[PDB]
Length: 49
Length: 56
Image 1 (cartoon, each protein chain N blue to C red):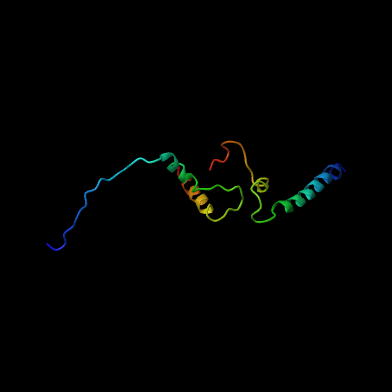
Image 2 (cartoon, chains in turn orange, purple; image 1 turned 45 degrees about the vertical axis):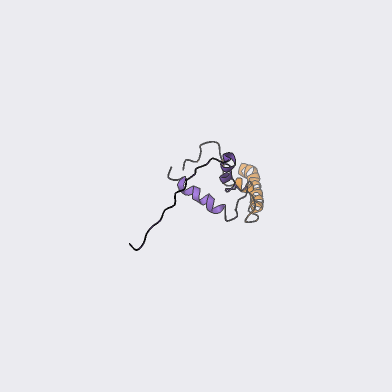
């Protein structure tokens, strides 16, 4: 029952992730930082191409 | 002796007026947006860089 114990919170955290994923897309012309959660940014000299 | 060209003698002047305004002025022709979708006049400046950044 450890799968029924541990992955139950992993189900609801994935279920809550589907709630915030609806929030981010918003308007077409929405934001330059709210779109900076899914698509990534990094430190200096990461993107080679 | 049909078509006689002419010429005018006049000094051709590369003078030196106030330069530090004239240098700064082609910076303000290019804006920079803090938005995701832009406004269709920066968007063809932003595309023109992403060509010739892929050759140097």
